[PDB]
Image (cartoon, coloured by chain):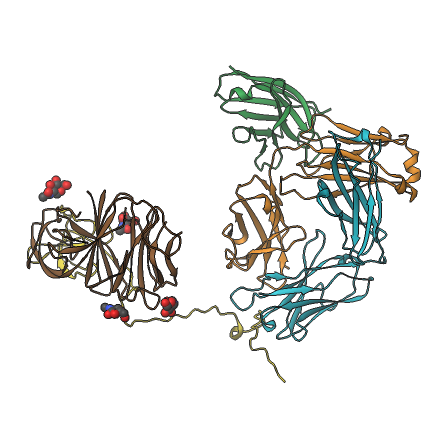
Chain colours: A cyan, B orange, C yellow, D brown, E green
């Protein structure tokens, strides 16, 4: 088997330089090759460079030549990429790929990635989310059912997990993608639906965990009549 | 440099229907063109690397052909788990160029949205900011008008929207919008409302709440 | 010390001369010992005519004579017919049967 | 169990059309009135001498194919013949085979890395005949099918296939496809209340036969010169 | 306003085929997708078919997709819907509607007028 292991979340100010890693394992390291790719929240793919660690040869895209460098060392069994002139547009998910397609008739296409590293470039600073619940009214019920939820605001940096703590209580839970404020802070929304026989009395509690610092935040939602 | 395009940009068909797509490139070639199966934020799966060629492990469910500047890519059958975006890639030369994408999804009968609105709370207003959310749940089409009607008057240019992908379990789709205001502008008005109209709905729907209650 | 790269890339480009261009080459090897020969080169190289003397070859069967349409009913698996004392009376056409 | 073979077992020797002619042919033939091995399928490994004559009578296609080889194992070359629902598949594989190959699970072989492959149309209360010869560097097959113990009526076998394989064949076995049986080779000859089906095995010998050709080039009678 | 009305329909024998016609005037027809709707006697409304500019075939509902076909004429504002091998189930009142939103992907049910179609 062949596998790739990537680092955790990394963030830096604009105009800086950053180091990233891609740990390779399994089989023989000398027979593998590594490539790097970037994936935004819906923009097209970008390919940074390519290296053959056994032989040390590398090449680049015109967009990233000069400003980016790759080094890989067998002894540490990981591949490295060097980045410079970071800017806000670099905020995306950064992936490392293995190009095994060079020695068996399969040519110049990857078939293995790691777990992917999310990256962000902003002037903000790390801090936890701000959460506030809402109070639906009984007159607002629809078809004998109602919904409750929470909004997550003012957290940085990502990734962020928004959910309800545990159990089947999560029935009818529904969440939507994140948005980024002009101040440099992320946001999220969540909702859960409840029938008449369980709304209010169930005492629903929304939860958030800012795993870059592993800070847990929770809040209660209460209807009214 | 090499540039390419894909047409059409989106496909919709029922479960088990045949699907086909085509990709165009700048220069005429007969090999060294690839195809990919990609989903939002997920890893592509390789199906074709050279014109009409595939590896061990590629399912027989995919195929491709063509010559010159136009190459076709066909899928024998569609299922809900296949909701993804097909892509063409080319590597005759080092400046690898990647396709414009073609969405593929599931056709279904019209589903009426479940409509609800999301009035503010006190802790929200104490921060100086005000916002309200209007949600449409499990409706088929890509968008349905979510109109803010503060004081029974239409509003525009002051809301944010978020979107979900098609639900593979039942091929439905959801949408919502979020109004934003300051507490002063919030209290300048008295009645809040959101209106929804939809293809499967009998008539326009209005949901509202008031500052005095 | 050196730890060289055992392979190398041709890096073909227009600036290179004919001695450094991508010749796609195929080479064939053949075997002939203990041969129930399954591979044969020559094609049909065939022509036909009837009602006059002609030297004829039918998958071999070298002979001379005049060929005319027959009325004998050959079985599907039979190729050539013989009269009394093994005289080749009729032959099935390899192409038209 | 043994039973006598009637004039059955003759075949067209040399693909040459002859009409109203008596031809003295010296080839491998099944001697007239020879006692032949009789088995009930309602499949042991049997020696493959200079020739083998095979026949079967059944209504639900229990007999489905044959298998041959020098050692009849992966240690050397081997040949397989099997009839599918719509096609007959032939391969010379040297594969390792099951103790009692059963087809339904497809319990036929343990491993296959074949070298020669071929496919053609299928063979199809009904009486079936097969003959196998290996005089030259090829494997020859003859067969015939008629509606219907071996009847006393006459029948001449027509050539069916002439495979260009020069492997050593000394042992052979028959494939069975009863309605139900175990999915593993750990047992044999059990699994269902199969109907009345049986097959016969007869061995050819060097013999001189006088074959009678009618006006249409079909063999209608034969004489065994040593009987 | 976006006025629209039908023509045709009426009485036909079961198992036959007939054409339903719908037309408009005084306004541009291209900037909206043109759809169709159905109501069985006393039953709720139900979408039938719709046509678009690109001409990439059409879109239909479950009850009508495998039997019926739809078409439109952008240069004359005339749109048509085909009925094939009518059955007792399809005896109903049909509506001609505009997907009343400029160059829009979805649709909004603005039915202009309707007529009855019945099987003898
Ligand atoms: C050979 O080709 C000719 C012309 O197509 C055809 O008439 C004839 O039947 C063919 N014979 C065989 C044996 O394929
Ligand atoms: C085939 O091989 C077996 C096993 O080696 C041997 O006993 C037999 O004599 C061989 N037959 C021929 C015809 O060579
Ligand atoms: C297949 O297996 C046999 C052993 O049964 C071996 O001798 C042979 O080299 C293998 N490969 C081929 C192509 O026969
Ligand atoms: C030869 O075949 C024809 C046609 O089937 C038949 O009429 C004739 O009787 C046959 N010849 C003999 C000797 O039976």
Frontmost residue, C21 versus A152: A152
User: Which of B65/B12 is in front?
Assistant: B12
Q: Is residue B163 visible?
A: no
Measuring from the top left, give residue D64's x and y in whole percent.
30, 51
Asked where in the image residue E47 lies, by quadrant, the reply is top right
Direction from residue B96 to residue D102 in the image, left or right: left
Q: Is residue C69 above or below residue B89?
A: above
Q: Position of residue B98 (x, y in %)?
A: 63, 56
Give percent across and percent down for residue E107. 68, 32
Q: Residue at x 72, y 35 (%)?
A: B144
How many numbered badges does the structure rendering display?
0
Relative horizontal placement of residue D67, taking residue D7 as reference (left or right): right
Question: What residue sits 86% from the left and 58% below the top?
Answer: A125
Is B110 located above or below residue A162 in the figure? Answer: above
Would residue C1 be seen by someone viewing this image from the given angle? yes
Q: Residue at coordinates 16% horizontally, 62% vertically from top-left?
A: C62
Image side of residue B145 versus residue C93, left or right: right
Asked if A84 appears above or below A157 in the picture, the reply is: below
- From the viewer's perspective, tell me whether residue D114 is left or right of residue D146: right
């Amino acid at each position: 088997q062949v596998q790739l292991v990537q680092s955790g979340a990394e963030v830096k100010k604009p105009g800086s330089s950053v180091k990233v890693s891609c740990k390779a394992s399994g089989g023989t390291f000398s027979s593998y090759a590594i490539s790097w790719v970037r994936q935004a929240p819906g923009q097209g793919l970008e390919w940074m460079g390519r290296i053959i660690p056994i032989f040390g040869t590398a090449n680049y895209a015109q967009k990233f030549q000069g400003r980016v460098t790759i080094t890989a060392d067998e002894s540490t069994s990981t591949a490295y990429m060097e980045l410079s002139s970071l800017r806000s547009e670099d905020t995306a998910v950064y992936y490392c790929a293995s190009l095994a397609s060079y020695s068996s008739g399969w040519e110049d296409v990857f078939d293995i990635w790691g777990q992917g590293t999310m990256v962000t470039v902003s002037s903000a600073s790390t801090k936890g989310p701000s959460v506030f619940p809402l109070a639906p009214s009984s007159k607002s019920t629809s078809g004998g059912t109602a919904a409750l939820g929470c909004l997550v605001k003012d957290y940085f940096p990502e990734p962020v997990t928004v959910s309800w703590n545990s159990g089947a209580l999560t029935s009818g839970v529904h969440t939507f993608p994140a948005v980024l404020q002009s101040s440099g802070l992320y946001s999220l929304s969540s909702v859960v639906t409840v029938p008449s026989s369980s709304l209010g009395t169930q005492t629903y509690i929304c939860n958030v965990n800012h795993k870059p610092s592993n800070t847990k935040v929770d809040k209660k939602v209460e209807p009214k009549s | 440099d090499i540039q390419m395009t894909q047409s059409p940009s989106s496909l919709s068909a029922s479960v088990g229907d045949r699907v086909t797509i085509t990709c165009r490139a700048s220069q005429g070639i007969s090999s060294w063109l690839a195809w990919y199966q990609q989903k939002p934020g997920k890893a592509p799966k390789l199906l074709i690397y050279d014109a009409s060629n595939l590896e061990t492990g590629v399912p027989s469910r995919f195929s491709g052909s063509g010559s010159g500047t136009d190459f076709t890519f066909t899928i024998s059958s569609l299922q809900p788990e296949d909701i993804a975006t097909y892509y063409c890639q080319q590597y005759d030369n080092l400046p690898l160029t990647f396709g414009g994408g073609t969405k593929v999804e599931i056709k279904r009968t019209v589903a009426a949205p479940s409509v609800f609105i999301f009035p503010p709370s006190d802790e929200q207003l104490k921060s100086g900011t005000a916002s309200v959310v209007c949600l449409l749940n499990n409706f088929y089409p890509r968008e349905a008008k979510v109109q803010w009607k503060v004081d029974n008057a239409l509003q525009s240019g002051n809301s944010q929207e978020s979107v979900t992908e098609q639900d593979s379990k039942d091929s439905t789709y959801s949408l919502s919008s979020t109004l934003t205001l300051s507490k002063a502008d919030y209290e300048k008005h008295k009645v809040y409302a959101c209106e929804v109209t939809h293809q499967g709905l009998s008539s326009p729907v209005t949901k509202s709440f008031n500052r005095g209650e | 010390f050196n730890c060289y790269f055992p392979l190398r890339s041709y890096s073909f480009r227009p600036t290179y001369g004919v001695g450094h261009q991508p010749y796609r080459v195929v080479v064939l090897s053949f075997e002939l010992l203990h041969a129930p020969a399954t591979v044969c080169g020559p094609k049909k190289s065939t022509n036909l005519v009837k009602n006059k003397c002609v030297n004829f070859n039918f998958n071999g069967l070298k002979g001379t004579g005049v060929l005319t349409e027959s009325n004998k009913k050959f079985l599907p698996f039979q190729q050539f017919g013989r009269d009394i004392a093994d005289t080749t009376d009729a032959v099935r056409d390899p192409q038209t049967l | 169990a043994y039973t006598n073979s009637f004039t059955r077992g003759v075949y067209y020797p040399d693909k040459v059309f002859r009409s109203s002619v008596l031809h003295s042919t010296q080839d491998l033939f099944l001697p007239f009135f020879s006692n032949v091995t009789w088995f009930h399928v309602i499949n042991p490994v049997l020696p493959f001498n200079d020739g083998v004559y095979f026949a079967s009578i059944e209504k639900s296609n229990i007999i489905r194919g044959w298998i041959f080889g020098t050692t009849l194992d992966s240690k050397t070359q081997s040949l397989l013949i099997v009839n599918n629902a719509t096609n007959v598949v032939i391969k010379v594989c040297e594969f390792q085979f099951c103790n009692d190959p059963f087809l339904d699970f497809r319990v036929y072989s343990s491993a296959n890395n074949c070298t020669f492959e071929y496919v053609s149309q299928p063979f199809l209360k009904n009486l079936r005949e097969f003959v196998f010869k290996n005089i030259d560097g090829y494997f020859k097959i003859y067969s015939k099918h008629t509606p219907i113990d071996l009847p006393q009526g006459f029948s001449a076998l027509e050539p069916l296939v002439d495979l260009p394989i020069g492997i050593n064949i000394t042992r052979f076995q028959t494939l069975l496809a009863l309605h139900r049986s175990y999915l593993t080779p750990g047992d044999s000859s059990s699994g269902w209340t199969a109907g009345a089906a049986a097959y016969y095995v007869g061995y050819l010998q060097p013999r001189t036969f006088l074959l009678k050709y009618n006006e249409n080039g079909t063999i209608t009678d034969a004489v065994d010169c040593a009987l | 306003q976006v006025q629209l009305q039908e023509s045709g329909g009426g009485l036909v024998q079961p198992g036959g085929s007939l054409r339903l016609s719908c037309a408009a005037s005084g306004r541009t027809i291209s900037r909206y997708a043109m759809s169709w709707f159905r109501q069985a006697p006393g039953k709720e409304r139900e979408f039938v078919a719709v046509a678009r500019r690109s001409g990439d075939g059409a879109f239909y509902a479950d009850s009508v997709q495998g039997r019926f076909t739809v078409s439109r004429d952008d240069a004359k504002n005339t749109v048509y819907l085909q009925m094939n091998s009518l059955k007792p189930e399809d005896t109903a009142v049909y509506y001609c509607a505009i997907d009343s939103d400029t160059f829009y992907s979805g649709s909004y049910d603005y039915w202009g007028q309707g007529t009855q179609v019945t099987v003898s």
